[PDB]
Amino acid sequence: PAQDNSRFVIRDRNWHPKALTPDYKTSIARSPRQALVSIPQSISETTGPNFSHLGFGAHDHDLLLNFGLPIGERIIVAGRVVDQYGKPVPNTLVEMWQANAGGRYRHKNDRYLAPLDPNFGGVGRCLTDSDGYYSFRTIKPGPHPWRNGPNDWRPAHIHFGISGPSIATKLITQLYFEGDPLIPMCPIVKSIANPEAVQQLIAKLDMNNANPMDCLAYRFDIVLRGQRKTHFE
Amino acid sequence: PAQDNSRFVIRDRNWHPKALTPDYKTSIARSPRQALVSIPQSISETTGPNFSHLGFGAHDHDLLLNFGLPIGERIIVAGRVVDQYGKPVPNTLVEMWQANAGGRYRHKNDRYLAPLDPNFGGVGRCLTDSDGYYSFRTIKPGPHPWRNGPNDWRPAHIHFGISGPSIATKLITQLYFEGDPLIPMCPIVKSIANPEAVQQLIAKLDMNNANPMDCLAYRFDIVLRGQRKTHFE
Amino acid sequence: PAQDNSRFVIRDRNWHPKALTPDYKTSIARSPRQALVSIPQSISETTGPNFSHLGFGAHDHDLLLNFGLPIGERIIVAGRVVDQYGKPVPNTLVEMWQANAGGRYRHKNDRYLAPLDPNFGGVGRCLTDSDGYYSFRTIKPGPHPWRNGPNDWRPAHIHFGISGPSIATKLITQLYFEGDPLIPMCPIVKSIANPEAVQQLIAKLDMNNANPMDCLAYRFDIVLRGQRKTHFE
Amino acid sequence: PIELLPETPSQTAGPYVHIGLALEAAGNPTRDQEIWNRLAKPDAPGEHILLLGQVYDGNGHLVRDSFLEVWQADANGEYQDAYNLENAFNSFGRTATTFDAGEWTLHTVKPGVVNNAAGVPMAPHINISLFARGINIHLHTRLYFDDEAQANAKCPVLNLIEQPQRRETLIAKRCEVDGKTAYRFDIRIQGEGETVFFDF
Amino acid sequence: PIELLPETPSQTAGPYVHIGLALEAAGNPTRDQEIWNRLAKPDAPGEHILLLGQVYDGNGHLVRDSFLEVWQADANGEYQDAYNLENAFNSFGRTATTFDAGEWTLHTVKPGVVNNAAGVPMAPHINISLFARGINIHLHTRLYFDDEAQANAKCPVLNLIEQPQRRETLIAKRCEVDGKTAYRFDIRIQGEGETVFFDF
Amino acid sequence: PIELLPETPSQTAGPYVHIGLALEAAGNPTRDQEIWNRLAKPDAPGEHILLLGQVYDGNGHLVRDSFLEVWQADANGEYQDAYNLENAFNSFGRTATTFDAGEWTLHTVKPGVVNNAAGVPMAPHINISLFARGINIHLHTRLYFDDEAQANAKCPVLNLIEQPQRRETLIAKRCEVDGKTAYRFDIRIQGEGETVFFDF
Amino acid sequence: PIELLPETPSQTAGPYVHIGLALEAAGNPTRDQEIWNRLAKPDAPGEHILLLGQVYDGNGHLVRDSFLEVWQADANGEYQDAYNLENAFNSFGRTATTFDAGEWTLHTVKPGVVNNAAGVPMAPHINISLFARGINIHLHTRLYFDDEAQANAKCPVLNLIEQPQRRETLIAKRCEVDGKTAYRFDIRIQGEGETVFFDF
Ligand SMILES: [Fe+3]
Ligand SMILES: [Fe+3]
Ligand SMILES: [Fe+3]
Ligand SMILES: [Fe+3]
């Protein structure tokens, strides 16, 4: 079983978005009004599941084939998962979901008038390699309207979930694409106070990883909380 | 019949791209080696067709309907046609053509592996109104690979053709989309030596023209050669 | 036998010197007028010879002993060979050639009036180590006049050829010395449009590697095309 | 001072979380192997229990789009990190609430006792992480049991909560569902009876 | 000096110009009304002629993806700007070269004479604009007729071209096609026999 | 966008390349082991052939100071990368043109067929890289055989060359030297019949 | 992106709004023609009704300095934009709450049905805008009728309000004042039973 041998650098809650960010309407009724209780790290918090033995399908990470071919811009999304100290996070679970090229989600509740793509599902998962690298093949999602302000549009984005070494490092975030003019107008993006933090969520075009006459590539690296050994405890 | 009643400001051939722009390989064998011969303007050059009586179909300008619904980001591309003096150019012919959401064109010669959309043709036409306004409804095209250098990608773009009042004003150009990271890397875009000139081809996101929960909008204004009355000739 | 398991980053032909650079006269008649034809990489382009088994002489890399002692400034030229990703390139072949201290080459065709040095050949070779390191010991070459413009002088230089992992990586270049005032005046240097690019060819004085009371040292690192594994092909 | 690389910022899970993390729940075709709500196989050692609950917003309305992640020890008070569907017991799982099912359910075993870093035993508990549209950064909590009063009184973690009244928000109420031992754990994100959430 | 708004910069028509401007040629379904290669209906006054030609690149290879627009006066030397498919004659038209058809063709009438700004007569001519992939800004030329030697000699435009040798590049050679009066006009974009192109 | 470290920029090999890479040719003492123009040992399997050619500049004048590097498969279509003078066949070799000898020679065997990345066979070919004073960055080309029309017609590489006339520049012409099987491959850097050069 | 000129920023009406927009209410001499709370004259077609309400702040205290403006269709579902005191019905009117009167009143007719932009009928409703000291930007709301349960159930606008509980806040309660048909519509600006406010 798991062992209590590590400590995780405390989260900077001024870096992450706050719970109450009024322009993002839904957060008003879904943010706690009491202060969070801080607790010392114990084995309960410093351990977590290891997915090295989950049976992954051959096309788990290939959105072009896991659902003919979908319509849309063919891209590879890749990067590395490292910690705050810059150490790679090997064999960790990376899960992603997105809309189709038209910004339509394959979910009941999505009534947007842009059609479903018969060949597109939009769900993927990948286990990082020995070096902390992951990659997915998909089509670039389209922006999509939502009922927030009267004319709000989320920039094109891919949802991401990363496990890391413990429940303490588990994170859900969103990737945005370089140059998208919708970025700065989005109230969900604006939930983040430091513009420097917003920069970390922007995937960069990566011509070096592209397959000529095939698909383009985007680079998105992820940094989880720093892990250290316990000392003088 | 037409009458010679106007002069057009001479073209700035240092503003427009030059004929020989070697990084754009096909331009090497398709650029004249002798100098152009300047001639004075006569009736032959200062008149042109007037398309006010062409019978346009109901959806000539609506690419969502003119070919189910196409897959991709729904947008309106609108703007105004003016001359160098800032005067509207009414009842003028604007024609456009583009690829589908995946960068695939509906032409025999287009062998790119991205699938065609059974509901998208990619051709439009619209006559400017009394104020010089035009608009089209379409989907945002995807970038596409082409055999120039070993890893060349055109930025998402739409081809435009504008008639104007004479054969002296007739122009063919391409619209690019605000923030596209591919813009600066394009040998075709780079056929234009002046950066200020390049900026004139970028369509700006126009939230004011969007239809909430439906489609986004882009603004692209076009400037034709200034038209003046003859004097002391 | 070799196998096709890698891809190389496409070269930037705007970074490397163009074919036609008129000030460098010999280029006028030896530059192709048609555009290069871009082809996809195959096993023919992504493999190349490994010189691990060539039998090198004990002084292959020592121009002080490989031909009394030569006259001139005793120096070591050392550095590392890495790819664009920063990965070292081990066991690669590095070859160099240069003039003597007076700028005279040991070649029939060299009719410059500076005498030959009876103890100087000017040819060297070295296979990089496991860390991509190489080194040579020689004497600093002198500048030499050449028939280009009426008073053209090559900055003191050393010719380099580096093999790399494949024929796609192979490269021939020239090393120049930090501070030489002739550098900015050379049409050959000038064949390179980007000033940032010229900096990459300048060897830096390296006092840390020098042998006190014996010889000085220069550092010259080389970067070859970035190598990556194929994906989704 | 010393500054490390900043952690990638969190973002809400959004309304369609289920299509990525709860395939079945989303009414979409699932893959061969899915991480779900059945931590224990019928043959796993320990007392087999059923956990259920509802999530409420600040207006007292059900949250029908939440996603929950759980982590707990086995019956021995041991954390089993090697996730495998072949295992009789997994320490990790996932559950959700949908428009279809406003209540979540988890099939597991009562966790054994674990000691904190100082070597003091914590009462049996399940670590929970809550995600949903409107939640910018996920909320952490713990589920304790009402039938472990003696233990709860001495838990060093529960004892960190300044006000006793707040401590009770962490206690699941024991019941029975189809003659089975069940515990009900409702989470109130905001307002009256607001559930305690931690930072660590 | 005084500077006005800059003109929108030109760009190549690109390889698929056909889909936007030559539907049929492109082999895609056409719309009701299309601007094409027949300027004169059989009952149009004047001499009915056939125009054809090929376009050559710098290497002497056929340009199979060109697009050409033409503007000319009617038989009476009048420019008919009101475009209408109902008209017996339109002064404007469009043609192309394709992979299938390496030669373009135009059905029209021999244009009447028109005066320049200074009141001097110009020899009968057709104004041409050429577009294609590889051409950043369209090329302007004029087509004159070999059976108009006298007029050609006095043309104030033809006369601006310094070298007589270059002047010939602009003269269409009379022939016959299926016993119909035709004129062949080949365009050479670059090199030996390079056609004259204008600026105005 | 992501930008990697910049590749070290290329420079011309200069007038004296022979002293560094073609010792013999340069008329200077050679070392124990040199990389030269004999890729095949008498006893290497395959059709033994002699390759020869001249290199011309833009004015049609001979280039008497070029340096060439070759890379080819063996008779079995296999690339032998482990260079060793003991090998009966090495896939790599070097040759040149000098004031003394304006024609280069190479002794090898006709290469076997290899597949492109897509799994389609390429016609037998030799990869060549050309260096010389006046050439800022080396030129890449391929040598094909006139006696392999069937293969050549299907080569996916040869087929990437738009104009058929340009394809012939890559075909070596069969002949005999001393009754030995030879092929002549002249390279034209610039002008009339300019050789196709690749970028990859 | 494209930026237009910015809209002039809003400012609270202030405590003396009545002097500018509700002269009588302010107890100051009125002018010849004033815009007030009588939308319909006794002879106007449709069901004549009395509307009344109170305005509450977050502490549950009466807001005695509010100013309200209403917009509604006539009995036939038509908006009468031409304001004139001579008219039998005006679609617009004004009302207020004062120290003297903590309740506002309006004399109108039950409005007919109007379709939304998508052609779907909306239940009978009155458009309201509220202004007062402490309100930086006016608040928008709608008043619907309890005796129109059927229409209400299907209103495209009422149906945009996520929580049914919240919809109830927009339903005026039918009653009778001096044995005349009336409806009571109280507004709670903040807290318990807070009224839905719109953005458009
Ligand atoms: Fe989303
Ligand atoms: Fe295009
Ligand atoms: Fe040299
Ligand atoms: Fe005031």
Image (cartoon, coloured by chain):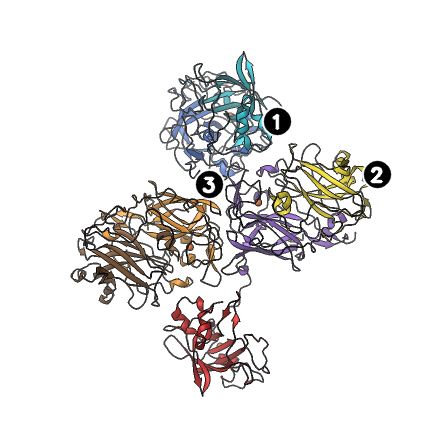
Chain colours: A orange, B purple, C blue, D brown, E yellow, F cyan, G red
Q: Which residue is mark 2?
A: E150
Q: Nearer the viewer, residue E107 or A51?
A: E107
Q: Chain of mark 1?
A: F
Q: Is residue G145 above or below residue C39?
A: below
Mark 2 neighbour density, 10 Å: few (under 14) some (14–19) many (20 or more):
few
x and y, in percent, of residue F17 in the image: 50, 23
x and y, in percent, of residue F58 in the image: 61, 26
Q: Identify residue type, mark 1.
A: Gly
Say which quadrant the C terminus of chain C sits in.
top left
Residue at far bottom of view: G178
Q: Identify residue type, mark 2.
A: Gln
Q: Is residue B216 left or right of residue E50?
A: left
Say which quadrant the N terminus of chain C sits in.
top left
Instruction: Please tell me in which quarter of the rendered image ligand 2 is found.
Output: top right
Mark 3 neighbour density, 10 Å: few (under 14) some (14–19) many (20 or more):
some
Q: Tell me, yes or no, whether the two marked residues, 3 and 1, touch with CB atoms within 8 Å.
A: no
Q: Which residue is mark 3?
A: A210
x and y, in percent, of residue G42 in the image: 54, 85
Q: Is residue D51 visible?
A: yes
Q: Is residue G97 visible?
A: no
Identified at 46% across, 69% down, the residue is G154
Q: Quadrant of residue B5?
A: bottom right
Q: Which residue is mark 1?
A: F193
Secondary element at image label 1: loop
Mark 1 neighbour density, 10 Å: few (under 14) some (14–19) many (20 or more):
few
Identified at 38% across, 60% down, the residue is D134
Q: Chain of mark 3?
A: A
Q: Identify residue type, mark 3.
A: Ala
Residue at far right of view: E150
Residue at far left of view: D150
Q: Nearer the viewer, residue C43 or G114?
A: G114
